[PDB]
Image: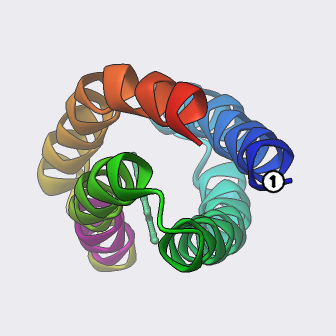
Amino acid sequence: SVKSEYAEAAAVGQEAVAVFNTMKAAFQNGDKEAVAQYLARLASLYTRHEELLNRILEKARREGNKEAVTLMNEFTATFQTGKSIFNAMVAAFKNGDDDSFESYLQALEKVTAKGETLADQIAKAL
Ligand SMILES: O=C(O)c1cc2cc(Cl)sc2[nH]1
């Protein structure tokens, strides 16, 4: 069902949370080789998550599930805020700008924390 597809999407999201925290530890420790690898892993995970989310939103639309569509339109918008911040973070890493990397990292954490009550609301709406 769309509900089990959302649980699968939620797990991919939690995987990115896990890798992100390991990445934050590596950044603080100065292990740039590790950070580079974790950033590649996160890019792939976010690409996957975004794709599942779109398939969930399109399915909710075809199902006429107006409330789920409303919530998923909001949630995908916020996902794109996180994605833009992540991409800027990756650029800061390429550029050697640890000040910008720190800023983007904290922002990406707060955008993720904010978007969690909605993530739970979608599970219940589908
Ligand atoms: O690159 C992406 O698509 C992407 C990165 C992040 C971080 C988030 Cl929280 S949501 C999100 N999406």
Say above or below: 90 vs 6: below
Q: Looking at the picture, how far across and down is residue 60, in whole percent?
A: 55, 65
Q: Nearer the viewer, residue 37 or 29?
A: 37
Answer left or right for 44 relative to 29: right
Answer left or right for 35 relative to 88: right
Tell me the quarter of the image containing the C terminus: top right
Say above or below: 69 vs 20: below
The residue drawn where x is 35% and y is 66% is 83
The residue drawn where x is 68% and y is 55% is 38
Answer left or right for 1 relative to 27: right
Q: Nearer the viewer, residue 70 or 111?
A: 70
Q: Nearer the viewer, residue 119 or 46?
A: 119
The amino acid type found where label 1 is placed reads Glu
**Mark 1 surroundings within 10 Å by alpha-carbon count, few (fewer than 14), some (14 through 19), many (20 or more):** some
The residue drawn where x is 62% and y is 65% is 56
Q: Which residues are magenta?
A: 83-92
The residue drawn where x is 27% and y is 78% is 95
Kindly give the residue lying farthest to the front in the view shown: 64
Q: Specify whether residue 86 is painted magenta.
A: yes
Within the image, what quadrant is residue 100 found in?
A: bottom left
Mark 1 lies on a secondary structure that is: helix
Say above or below: 101 vs 53: above
Within the image, what quadrant is residue 54 found in?
A: bottom right
Quadrant of ligand 1 in image: bottom left
Q: Looking at the picture, how far across and down is residue 51, in whole percent?
A: 63, 77
Mark 1 lies on residue: 5
Q: Specify whether residue 4 is painted magenta.
A: no
Within the image, what quadrant is residue 45 found in?
A: bottom right
